[PDB]
Image: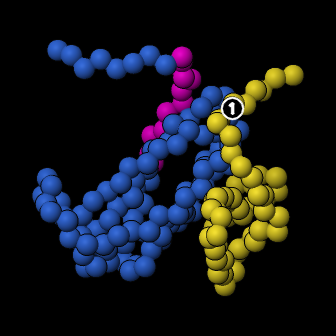
Chain colours: A yellow, B blue
Amino acid sequence: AIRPKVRDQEGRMNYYWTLVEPGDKITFEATGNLVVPRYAFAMERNAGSGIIISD
Amino acid sequence: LSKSYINDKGKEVLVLWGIHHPSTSADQQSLYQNADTYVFVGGSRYSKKFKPEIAIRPKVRDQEGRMNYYWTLVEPGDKITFEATGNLVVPRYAFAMERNAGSGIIISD
């Protein structure tokens, strides 16, 4: 459908994320409209810190 | 159906609309004439596509269908677009408003 233009785009793109545990498989399947991953991120979380928005 | 509104009120506009889910395929066609319908509502920040779900629910206030109610706040200078081939309970009155720092609600006699 046609949405009001934002940055000259009448379409929209939704962004998704998931954390894949070690030894698990993630499967992608599509007949279209898939913005595939190219770079993923191996990481180990800490006990949560926060985010500071400041100059 | 295709109708658009641009907020020229200088403040936020609260827009509400409803989606109707008939009880039977007969009821769908008797109201909207089209069997396979959709509703789309789009703004600079809102975007949702609605698909009517037709089935007989237990009667509540003598209604076997259901109607879902939705709202969004349209920022100044933005456009909200409605598109439908049926099942759209369109806005008629919207509300230009300016929110405060939140108060609360008292339920009392």
SS for dot 1: loop
Answer left or right for A15 relative to A6. Answer: left
Instruction: Find out whether residue A28 is within the magenta segment.
Output: no
Task: Give the residue drawn at x 17%, y 60%.
Answer: B63
What residue range appears in magenta? B91-101
Task: Give the residue drawn at x 66%, y 81%.
Answer: A30
- Above or below — where is B29 with respect to B46? below
Residue A31 or B40: which is nearer the viewer?
A31
Horizontal and vertical percent position of residue A21: 62, 62
What's under tag 1, amino acid-wise? Ser
- Above or below — where is A29 with respect to A15? below
Horizontal and vertical percent position of residue B32: 37, 72
Task: Give the residue drawn at x 60%, y 40%.
Answer: B74
* Residue indicated by mark 1: A49
Horizontal and vertical percent position of residue B10: 66, 28
Figure quadrant of residue B87: bottom left
Instruction: Find out whether residue B97 is within the magenta segment.
Output: yes
**Magenta highlight: main SS:** loop
Task: Give the residue drawn at x 49%, y 33%.
Answer: B95
Q: Residue furthest bottom?
A: A31
Q: Chain of mark 1?
A: A
Answer left or right for B37 relative to A19. Answer: left
Residue B107 or A29: which is nearer the viewer?
A29
